[PDB]
Image 1 (tube, rainbow, N blue to C red):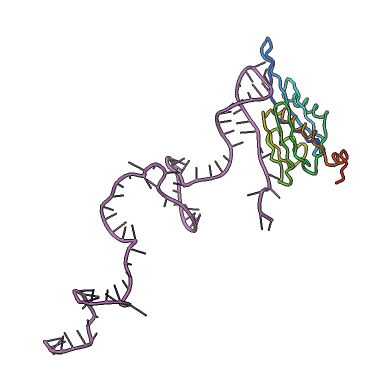
Image 2: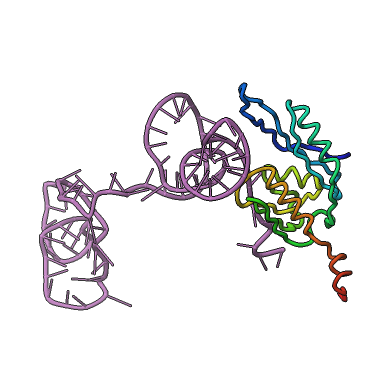
Length: 152
RNA sequence: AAUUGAAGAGUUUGAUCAUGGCUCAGAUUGAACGCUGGCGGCAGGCCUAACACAUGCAAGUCGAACGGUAACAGGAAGAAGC
């Protein structure tokens, strides 16, 4: 029900005096399908501990979205460290087209139809953060109406 | 009811990010090659040497234009091995 899924796991090194301390880092996302998307990175000495810590971190700091019935109400562009993401409402289209490290996060967010493309360095963590920031910056028509004096 | 519309992955380093190129996952062709190979329908078949060509054929028709008859179906002008 919590719609949890990780994206990639990578191992790191410390290069200590006695050799190398091989640790592990994770990347997980959590959601339900009506917003409430969270992410977690997670570090540990072992892969299972790292992914558990990533899931626990994703459990908190969960930010909601103002999604339409199955997509966004407007195209959006998200920018981050070295990754740029473009989202288009893409009505019907019997599904998404997004690629790695991005299709996972929206299938977690629950939006079935969306045109998602990534320009720039394809760092999973950076593209996920860019997508989260773009979703946060996205605004709903009801919100903009109440802000601006709808009169529509 | 007549363009409703987009995927990424690996690689610099003890590990990170970015820049940056390289490679791969798709279609597609007048395709060639290797292996294999049953049938039918449709389409295609010198991209290179506008290099050179044996041979045969691709533009003749009209006698209702004409002088003509080489023909010859020759009835028929004539004759007959009858």
